[PDB]
Image (cartoon, rainbow over all chains, first blue to last red; front, side, top):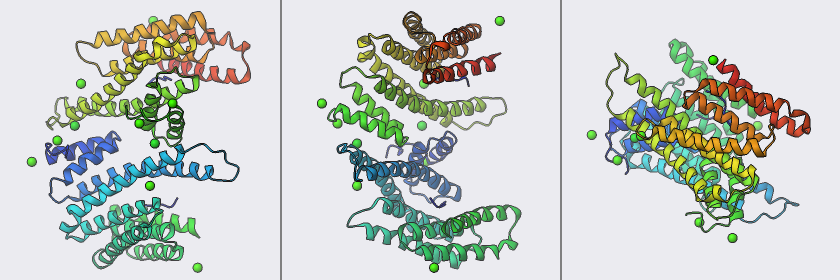
Length: 5
Length: 5
Length: 236
Length: 236
Ligand SMILES: [Ca+2]
Ligand SMILES: [Ca+2]
Ligand SMILES: [Ca+2]
Ligand SMILES: [Ca+2]
Ligand SMILES: [Ca+2]
Ligand SMILES: [Ca+2]
Ligand SMILES: [Ca+2]
Ligand SMILES: [Ca+2]
Ligand SMILES: [Cl-]
Ligand SMILES: [Cl-]
């Protein structure tokens, strides 16, 4: 999964 | 802390 | 509200305690109580609200993914029939997740966004609105999926427009908003080229502004820039 | 019972799903429902019950320890007064923990222990009874602390007596019971010499019986023996 903040 | 199961 | 009888300051104090104890459901309930006092939130308080709910919904999302994968395998050729239980339990988790999202969106709508006038606060809340519609989109399969996707898009777009006008390209909120909106494009909107373009343009415009920053601000901005780079590496 | 309308087999199926999803509160609720159907539990089912509640109470214990340490620091000389909130929140977590313990003890008393006739099941449940009284003892400070400690001791002692008569010294249940009762001695009963003696005698009697075991049984027994050794290393 890609990075989110 | 000591080990328990 | 079960928190109606507790002082605002006490709710904030206990949210911090709950964070230290990794009790994120409690943290979220405390911060919901604090919001419902009706006063605007400080920067610190906004971050406590976001941390709490991010952790709660993050665990729900991870669980939903596990259950969804099991359910998908059950519907393959050669799979033995095991009855309605996998679907039922996936649905239970999904309903709880949707409830958390609806709670957050309700706080934003009553009345955090409408009273947020400063760019930093308004962008922060609109990013949250995009995020929680995005989580709803992840599990949506019905007549309303398009409308949920458009609600996420609209919130992110308003936040982007404000951030570009009012914040420097290295601002952490701006960077984190762009990171997440880029993921929206890739994972939700079926727009990988837009995702990649956004991540790259954001990275490059931030790099050009790093020279203006203190050591501490540089550390903050570069950390998020690395996440943009990480996604770009994943996608290219 | 909210689970009264769900089939026993469906509760067990969903407990396994919940485990895979790391949803331990759900797992525990499913297994409580299963127990309340009134039938005895298989070996596998007993382990699902214990896993679920161990994980729930384990998180509560970790949180309680964090909060207790903060509270202790607040009562040191030179510490600024911060009001009742730390104590209140520690008390909230404590009350929830005690509720979980009382729930488990209630299942054991109604009616798991009284219907458990085979040594493997009866020892398993009595070990659980000792464990959950031990968790209550960890947080007890009042008029009943001695009685809680004695309840733990009594349950562990009955389990030890059965296990020594009816099970080989390498049996995993027997080994795990001894491990935990030794920790009870060290951490609860202020009896470190008894703790050390128990751990060493248990280890040595198991070592002497390893030659009787299959490869798979050897792996199981030696893993727990290593925990005994680890505690001995910590304590000596
Ligand atoms: Ca209240
Ligand atoms: Ca007040
Ligand atoms: Ca649904
Ligand atoms: Ca292309
Ligand atoms: Ca039911
Ligand atoms: Ca039935
Ligand atoms: Ca108490
Ligand atoms: Ca000695
Ligand atoms: Cl369910
Ligand atoms: Cl509280």
